[PDB]
Image (cartoon, rainbow, N blue to C red):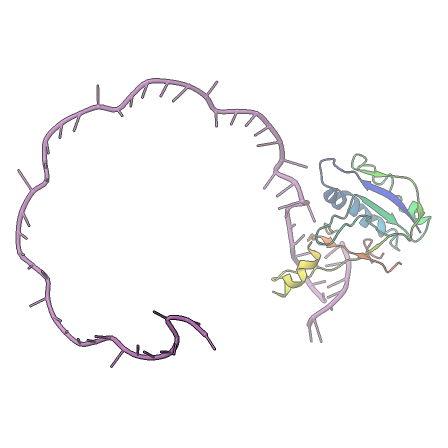
Length: 155
RNA sequence: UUUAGAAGGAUUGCCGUCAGGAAAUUAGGUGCGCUUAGCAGUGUACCGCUAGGCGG
C-alpha cells in the first residue's frame, strides 16, 4: 500500500487546477476502471477551510505495492512533462488523508434552502466532463480518515 | 436636601391704490504631464436518482 509522487509544477502559465482537471483526472478516470479496486488519491496540502487549493503535489496511493505498476501513471502522463513530473519511487503509505465526495446540493431550478447548504462545499473543486451524456460539473473534496477509493478515487 | 415648592394667556380681525433704471466700454501675454503593469482569482457550480446521501 504505497504511493507515487506526481507534482504539478508551480508556475508554468496555466493554473494547477486546470492542469489536473484537464490532463490528470480524465487519465485517472480512464485508468481506474482498469484498476477495479481504485488505488487511492491523496492531495497533500489541501490547506485551510476558509480558502484552500487542492495543492501542488498529488500523491496517488494504492492498497498494494504492485498495483501501482499496473496502472502505470508514469509514461501515461508523459505529455505533461513540462507541467507534471512523475517521480519513480514507492513508499508504504498509510500516512496520508483519505478524500471524500461531499455532495454540494443542486440549483434552485433543478429541484432558499440551496444556498444554506451550498455555502459549505463551494469554498477543492476539480472539474469533470462526463464520459456519458455530457453535462459537466466540478466534484468537491474534503479531508477524512476512514482508511480503506471506489469510483474516481474517492471513497 | 438645588432663588426650594405652585401656576390655562386668551378671544376677534380686508393693507391698500400707482409707477421708464439708463447711457458707455480692448482682458491680455507665456508654457514638456510623465514613467509602469497577467483580467487574474479553477470562474464555475448539472444532469438525474419527503429529510438525508449518490452514477458521470
